[PDB]
Each structure stands twice: as C-alpha cells, then as structure tokens.
Amino acid sequence: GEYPTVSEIPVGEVRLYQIADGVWSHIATQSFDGAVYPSNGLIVRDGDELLLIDTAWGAKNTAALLAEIEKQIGLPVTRAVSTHFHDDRVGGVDVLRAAGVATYASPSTRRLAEVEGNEIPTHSLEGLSSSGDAVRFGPVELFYPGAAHSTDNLVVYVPSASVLYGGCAIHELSRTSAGNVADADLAEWPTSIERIQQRYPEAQFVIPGHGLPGGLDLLKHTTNVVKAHTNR
Ligand SMILES: [Cl-]
Ligand SMILES: [Cl-]
Ligand SMILES: [Zn+2]
Ligand SMILES: [Zn+2]
C-alpha cells in the first residue's frame, strides 16, 4: 500500500499502516515552526493484545490514535513505551494511563521528562542505561544505541517481522537537515548509528521518526545528514 502522507491525514487525525504481519506504524500530522509533517510511531501485536510505541503528541491526538487502533485493529493496547523524553513522544501518556494502558520508559527518559515538565511514563525500563544495552519486551527488543537525537533515545526492533523503528535517531531520505538538535549529541550520533547497524544488519524495514519508511540505507543517510550538520 501507498504510505500515508500529510495530504491523506488532516491535522488531528491518525492513520495506521500495516508494515508486516502484526506490525503497524501510526502516523499523525503535526505542526511545528511554520510547517506540517507526518510523525511515525509503532504498534506491535502481542498475543491478543497490542504494544504501542510512542504517543501521537498530545492528549487529543493520542485519544484519536486509540480510536483509530480500535477502528482498524480492535485489540486492546495494554502497554506503551516512549522512545525519548520529548513532548512529541511522551505527550499523551496521561491519556494512555487514564485508558488503562501501562506506560513505560527508561529511568533516563523519566528523569529528563520530569526536568522538562513533560508527562512521565509510570513504569521504569531497567537494563538500558549503557550504550549497546538491549532488553526483550514482549514482541520487541528495546535497544539503547547511545546518545544521538537525545541522550536517552531508544530504538525498537520486531524480530518476527524484521522491522526497526528508530524514532528521531533515524532520518527519512527526504530530510537534509539534522532536525531539532537542541538536546542531541552530535559527536556520538554516528557511533550510535553504527551500533544499530551492527546489531540489526538483517533489518528489512526501517521506520524513521518522521516520514517515509525505507531500508537500512536510512542509517547511512542519517550519518550523511549528521556529518553535514557537524561540518556546517
Ligand atoms: Cl540499568
Ligand atoms: Cl517480555
Ligand atoms: Zn526529540
Ligand atoms: Zn542520503
């Protein structure tokens, strides 16, 4: 199927895209600094339940995400993981919590969300504090590749489907800039990408934080973009 773009997704709405069996992305149109763009998260079937990766940025959008999941899939979301502390990825956690979803993040993410004044996932994910750390979490592996887009950023791999979701640590091909780098670690980002390459060389589908999916070429693209920004 054609991957949904901002022209299929009005502001405040959410669409799902089935990447593979029991794996979807969720896509929401967001507004920022004069522009609009499509933000991805992930949904992974976990027996007869669903694991959500990342909110849809804010209470209203995350409610709309839960509705679209019920419409298109119809299984209960029982757990959610936020991949870093920024408002776009934890904004909407209170809605998930109120709807009975167990919300998770690393202690690193929880700490930085609190400092920032953002919503804070309730449960803490142990075993991810050091670069290269990985932990199993139901139908996914969570991986802390090192600092990149942020110091806490996690990536998520679905072994059954060979899908890698990079959140904002991986850029789509149409991105030329490094994105919001206020909290990034530019010096460590290319090393962190190399850890991802080394761990998941078998990945077939790579989902960037924003925009169009691709393959492992997205990792090299991301390092190219990051180098360009470093050498500005
Ligand atoms: Cl730990
Ligand atoms: Cl588990
Ligand atoms: Zn961010
Ligand atoms: Zn490129």
Image: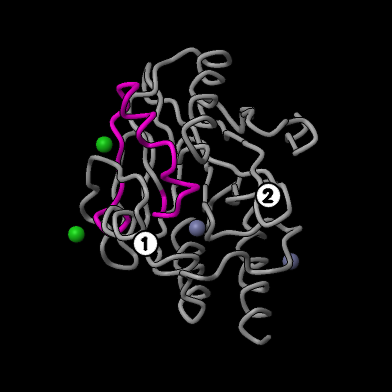
Residue 85's quadrant in the figure?
Answer: bottom left
For label 2, the residue is 214
What residue did someone put label 1 on? 152
Classify the position of the C terminus by image quarter: bottom right
Dot 1 falls on a residue whose secondary structure is: loop
Left or right, 5 with reference to 87: right
Magenta span includes 87: yes
Q: Is residue 73 above or below residue 207?
A: above
Residue at image location 77% in from the left, 30% down from the top: 8
Magenta segment boundaries in residue numbering: 83-109
- Mark closer to the chain start, 1 or 2: 1
Identify the colour scheme used.
one colour
Ligand 4 in which quarter: bottom right
Given residues 184 and 160, the one toward you in this image is 184
**Amino acid type, callout 1:** Asp
Mark carried by residue 47: none
